[PDB]
Image 1 (cartoon, rainbow over the protein chains, first blue to last red):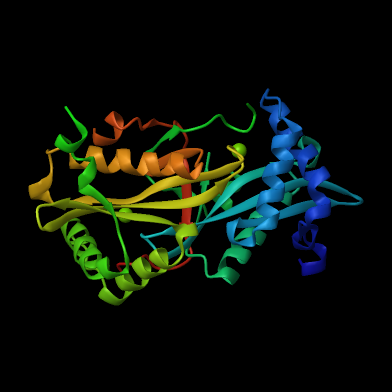
Image 2: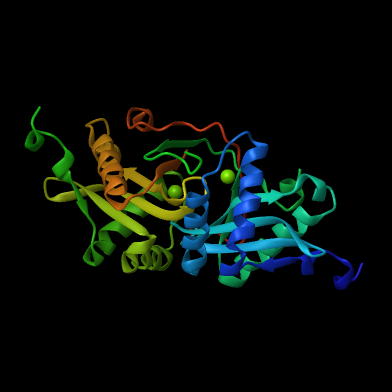
Amino acid sequence: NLYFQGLSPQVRTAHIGDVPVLVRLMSEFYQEAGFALPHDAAIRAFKALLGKPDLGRIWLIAEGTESVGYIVLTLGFSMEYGGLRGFVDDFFVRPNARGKGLGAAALQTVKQGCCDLGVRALLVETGVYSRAGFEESGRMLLGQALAPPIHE
Amino acid sequence: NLYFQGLSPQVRTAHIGDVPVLVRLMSEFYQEAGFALPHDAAIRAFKALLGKPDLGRIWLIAEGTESVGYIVLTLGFSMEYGGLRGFVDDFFVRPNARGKGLGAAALQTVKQGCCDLGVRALLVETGVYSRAGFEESGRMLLGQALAPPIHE
Ligand SMILES: [Mg+2]
Ligand SMILES: [Mg+2]
């Protein structure tokens, strides 16, 4: 199939004016998991990231006249690669918009963005991912919170 | 035991002049794993990180007149926390200097550094970690390389 027939044009860069829609989408994403998302905290986070491109990038996933999803890339240095690595830090497609290939398109867009930026690797914390070239790393992830998460 | 009797003063911030020692230590770290580390790539990586504090921080672990280890903190945005999270990105103590509590001191220093910076969480990819408050996150990590790692 040809480019215009596919879903790549449906994934677009997000701007400051998109914050209200991004907040709604993140709120839906959180509600689906049974969490309440404070609107101030969400606004703060999206504005912080949009205000400093060095931190990463956000794309919205469009269908008709609506954004029906979004994906967030965050960036950090990696000694293993001697350069930046990226994370698919958050990724949401509305339930009604799933199973249409939008998620796959979003991941391809982020991967292309990474290559364009000279990003050396792309990771995600967790089907759609496997087909996008994400495979299990085999590394045990440890952590500790130093502050409450955003939904608190 | 009192502060001066402990190992916290043994963990110090690294500067540009430390690059030759950092490269040797990273080379030892890599050789222990059976890898050869290109010296140009190592120099490039340490200089990049030391040149841009927004990317993270490096500490050296001192014993007598020698650095016997180092630890690297890298920083990235996290939507989950609505702020920066940190990674213990690399961590090496020379074999002869292990089992003396130096690793524990290094991790405490990084954790304090994170709190001072308003970093919201601290993660590590993988005993010493457990006692430093790192516990299994339960999240499967997926990834794909977009470029060769530093030892290639
Ligand atoms: Mg999340
Ligand atoms: Mg490493």
